Length: 326
DNA sequence: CCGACAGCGCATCAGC
DNA sequence: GCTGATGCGC
DNA sequence: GTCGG
Ligand SMILES: O=c1ccn([C@H]2C[C@H](O)[C@@H](COP(=O)(O)NP(=O)(O)OP(=O)(O)O)O2)c(=O)[nH]1
Ligand SMILES: [Cl-]
Ligand SMILES: [Cl-]
Ligand SMILES: [Cl-]
Ligand SMILES: [Cl-]
Ligand SMILES: [Mn+2]
Ligand SMILES: [Mn+2]
Ligand SMILES: [Mn+2]
Ligand SMILES: [Mn+2]
Ligand SMILES: [Mn+2]
Ligand code: NA
Ligand code: NA
Image (tube, rainbow, N blue to C red; front, side, top):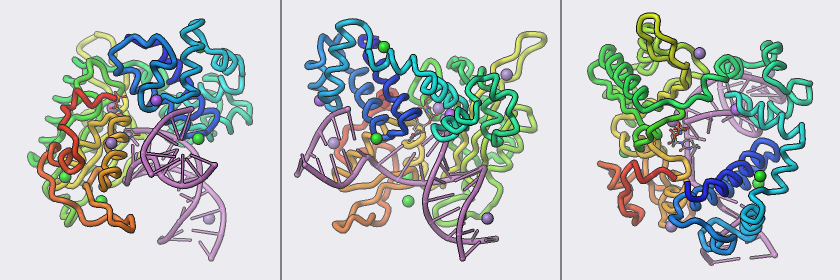
């Protein structure tokens, strides 16, 4: 982690602007700068050297000089001493609680894990589950565990219908030795951009996973996107595995490539790639890659048959999943 | 010195 | 009931 | 907070 010190400062700053300042752009700005720095193959010796990287400006340049000069950043040392900011930051760590709900709870006197446990009646379903699994969701998932999970999801999928195609994406597909959660991309021949022949496609898949006790809870659930919890099965008498977050997204079969490009990420990567697309005159989403008319309006979907094809349309050398971790 | 910053599914609410 | 703005998340 | 124009 050549510049682990600096990227942490930045990430902390991004989290602050997002959770406490509710300044989403500043948030993204720091994330981007932290991303470009993380891949910079040199140990940064100064804020000037860093400012040469696209994304780092005069403000981050100074913060970096200050950090390198003392190993600390005053603005952050203070933020850490502000109870309100500490509470808001902490509450946002619970799935379902955003900057808004956090600042609210703080106002109503709720600002500790304990305060939340006694006011479960003031949380919506999602916030309740997030609170319930707070601890577990903090633990990372070892790849070896992701592999055990993949077999269970894929095999349980096939058992509902041998025509489903379940693909694990997210950081898992990017090659991470550890993942924050499991992301599943699902496709079935009956669901395409031209029609939904069969209904409940996603339902039955969830239903099945719940039947075998793999899926333990639901944060949210719709026709195409499921957000819940799951747990690997444990052998006889051995300790129990941490509950884990699991996202399942059903995408039209004929749009798998745009969907798989989206779900593999990373998020910062997608951001850069989609920003670049616009620069070249295109707009990309999880379903398609359309051309941008002079008026701005997006045209019809262009033909796609691989992830690379999409990359071509924007003038970018194809980059493997493992090199998309920005 | 300005406006843009990627794109979208779900839960929830206010209003009609 | 619907529509659309908001919060929160991928 | 940063950047292209
Ligand atoms: O803001 C977002 C969030 C996610 N995504 C896409 C890309 C990301 O890789 C994918 C999965 O989302 P996760 O939040 O699961 N992140 P990821 O799997 O990359 O990392 P990890 O789960 O290990 O934190 O969803 C976006 O496009 N924008
Ligand atoms: Cl902002
Ligand atoms: Cl610090
Ligand atoms: Cl596609
Ligand atoms: Cl579309
Ligand atoms: Mn993930
Ligand atoms: Mn996820
Ligand atoms: Mn548990
Ligand atoms: Mn570009
Ligand atoms: Mn009402
Ligand atoms: Na720069
Ligand atoms: Na949260």
